[PDB]
Amino acid sequence: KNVTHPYWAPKTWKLRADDITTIMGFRAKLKGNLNHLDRPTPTVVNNAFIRGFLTKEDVMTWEVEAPYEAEYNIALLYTGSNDILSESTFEVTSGTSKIIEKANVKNWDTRPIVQRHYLKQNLLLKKGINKISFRLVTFGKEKTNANIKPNPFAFWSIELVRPEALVAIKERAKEIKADLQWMVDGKYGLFVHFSSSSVPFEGGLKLGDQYQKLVKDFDVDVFVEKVLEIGASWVTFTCAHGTQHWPGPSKTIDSIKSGFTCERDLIRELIDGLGKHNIRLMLYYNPNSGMEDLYGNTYGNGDQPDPSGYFNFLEAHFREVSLRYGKDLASTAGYIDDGGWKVYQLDPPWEKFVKAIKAGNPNAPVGFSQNLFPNLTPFSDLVVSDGSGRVPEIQPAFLFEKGGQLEGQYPASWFYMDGWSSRVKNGKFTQKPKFSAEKYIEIFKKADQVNMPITINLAMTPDVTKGHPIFNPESIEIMKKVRKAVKGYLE
Ligand SMILES: [Mg+2]
Image (cartoon, rainbow, N blue to C red; front, side, top):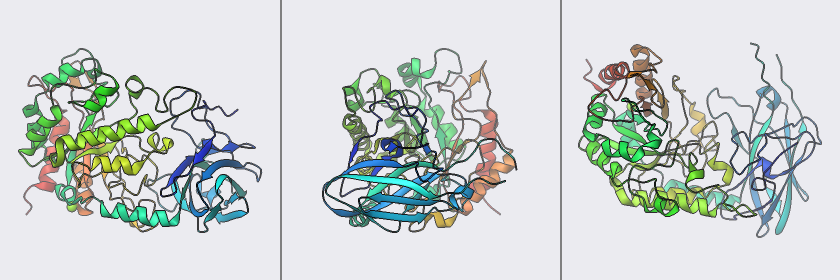
C-alpha cells in the first residue's frame, strides 16, 4: 500500500551530534496498519503524517547512525483528537532503552495544531547503526456537534538532540535573537503579493509570463504613496510567489538558470522609496514554488537523494541578498513560505539559513512560515502562518514559556483583508473585504493593545502604474479609518 519514490523511501539517518536532527515518520519502516499518503514522485507531499496506531503491533522503526555513544533527548510531533490523546501511551525503544509516556492533551484552541512533545526520559544510542522504534501501547478512541471526517492520532516526525547540544543551541539562539521593538511600535504593516499568477489591471499575460516588463514598468512613487496613505510602517513584498522570478540582480539565481532576475534593482528602489518615510522593507520568499523550473528536484537526480545542492542555493541566496542591501533591508526572510509543510521535510540546516539571513543585517527578523506546526527552529524570531481572512487568533501566553510549543518566538499576525493575490476581471476588483470597517478597527485595536504586530494584505494589481487603482478602493478606505482609530490623534 505505502508508496515512496526512492528519494523519500526509509533509509539510515546520519545523526548530527551537535545539532537537532529531525526524521519524518515516513522515513521509518512501517508494520501493521501504519500508512501515509502516496509519495510517488520527487516532489514533496505536504500530508506526510503516519496514521493507523490502533493496536500494539502497528510499529514504526527508524535506522539511525550515532557517531558515538550518548544520551539523546527525544521529541515527538503529532496531532489528533484529544479524546484519542487523553488515553494514548507512547513507547520509544532502542536496544534496551525504553521510554514510556502518556500523550499530551492539546489544551489551547489556537495554532499550533501539531504539537512538539519532549519526552522526560532520554534514550541511549550505541555507536554506529541503531534501530529506534515507536508505537502506542494504550489507545483512546473518538467520542460523541456532528461532522464526518475522523481525527485519528497522526504522527509527523521524531527529533533527536543531545541535551548538551540543546543547551548550547539555545544559547546561540538567545545571542542572535532579533529585537522586534520597531515592529511593535510600528503596530502594523502591509503585505503586498506581487504574485506570478496575477493578471494585470489593463489585461494581458499573467505576471509570471511578462515578469521583467512589469518590473521595468512598476512605478515606485505611485506605490509608496498608497503605502504611506494607509499608515503602514513596513511592507512585506512577495519575491517568487508561484515562480522563482526575483525582482532584482542575483548572482546566485543566475548561476542555476538564467531568465529569473532583473536588470532593474527594484528591491533597492523600494528600500529607498519607502525609507524616505521611515517605512521598512521585508521580503517574502517561496523556496518551493517553481523551483522545479530553476533548480530541479530538491533531492537532485541520480540514483540516491542528495539535498546539499538545494541547501547551498538557499544559503548562498539568503546570504547574497542580506549582504547586498545590508541594514537598509529589514529582512530577506520576513516570510519564508511553507517552512512547516515543505522545508521541514528535508531536515534542513536551519542555523546556516539564519546566519545567512542575518549576515548583512544582524537584527533582521527571521520568519519561517511554520503553518500549523510548533516552532520550526530555536533560531526563529516571529510566529508566522497564513491567517486567510479571519480574525487573528490570540495565542495564549503559556505557549511562549520555557518548554512551550512556541518558546523563542514573538506573536505576529499575517492575513488578508480582501485576498492574497489580486483577481481583477474587466477593470474591477473581484475580492471584496471580509469585514466591516468597525470590525477591522477592533482587530487592529486589540493587536495594538497586546503589542502583536499585524501584516495585512490588500490585493494589488501587478501593473503598478498611474493608470488605475493598484489597491481595491474599498480596502483602502477601510484602512484609512483603521489608521485614524489606531495611529491618529486620540482625545
Ligand atoms: Mg502596541
